[PDB]
Image (cartoon, protein in one colour):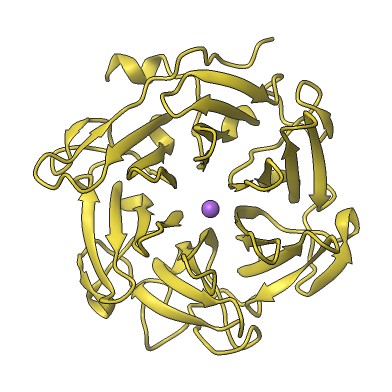
Length: 351
Ligand code: NA
């Protein structure tokens, strides 16, 4: 209903990443098949995918093409942005020093390889949805939503292989990669000790912690902790551990203080999960899909999916179905509000 929604330059942005060294915000503008780089205030810097048209082309920023990208991760040391180019079934790399877009894995077509281990474009994928970058070991962890697996790309050898999950669509939290299953994982974010990676397990409606040394995982909140086959213990309920009900969370972000932020996407809320107490509170949203800013208990979102955070504590949200990027300044409990962040200089894909 609002005038801001009519005039958005984004169409259904899926995810977000942030460069805190250089005050840059990366927006995956999924349904325009492009990446937008703005400053932390929404002012435009540069575009990757100017056509707006679904395609699969490497090269310079103006030649390059994506197909419904979602997840973005930032390599600070090398000034690179990893892209989960979902409907190209590829992992792609935006090079900001060389103004080049390169493909790191995948070949354009959906694979059936549940094991992997090939190099570069010879290794196929299946709807990669989110990524994160482990900086000491130079690994990209991939949420393969299409095979219910977490995969691992090594920067050093160019190998993409399965990292965890046997491929059955289940909420199964074992202690090895084979004895673990995922259910449409769509968000991954590393804890601050780099030993765990928190998982937004969408079709189980759970948040899970993948062990980066063993390959097993722990159930944190949401889902049925008893029957790995029940992908229906979903709902909307705050609490601790098994009390918690979520519905199809698509995004997750771990902050440096260890606190986990998530998008309870089909509940149109944004929740915070404490990794020690397993307590989940609601940070913003009512439960009704729509657009409204202000204080968070009255405020509204529409299928949010992606988060990024500054170190002064500003939490940006890809309010996907509203096609807006929003933000909340955390830890102002009585005064907490969700604002819409206008973007200046950002315009639709030119014909
Ligand atoms: Na991510």
